[PDB]
Length: 195
Image (cartoon, rainbow, N blue to C red):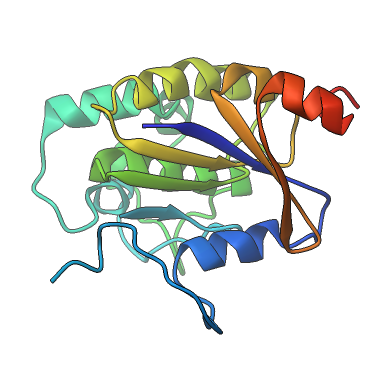
């Protein structure tokens, strides 16, 4: 249930840190238990599309629910996209289909993650490819997504400082290492968060 930001310079390893969070690197040593080693949704740094309908890009091996779909459509800012799609959800997307923008692909990925209702969400800079108004949408609906999240843990990697006061706690990373984790006052003493 914590709201935790991950920040640092372009190329400092933030996306690689997310890959570490996905278990996609080689652990040289140490112990890691996330309750999943007892005997998940993903928004990748570069969005990718499956070759299917927008609808099936949303379902992601699930049954179809259309109230959940209505709430997801409103919550994921997908009404302008539907409004500009030639057949709405029946538009063929992915390879050899309609060419979605990077922002539309990101919004589809966000909708995929919200629809999957996972316990852990990894967002790799999710509002970079969206406009300021859509970023405000992702702010309010994000806050009512984590709020919609019934106690779930949400990890929001971002390169932007715009909403670091508006998440709960920040962990600052640099050069592939964690530099500091802590309160606003702690990071004021770091003399970083103000900068």
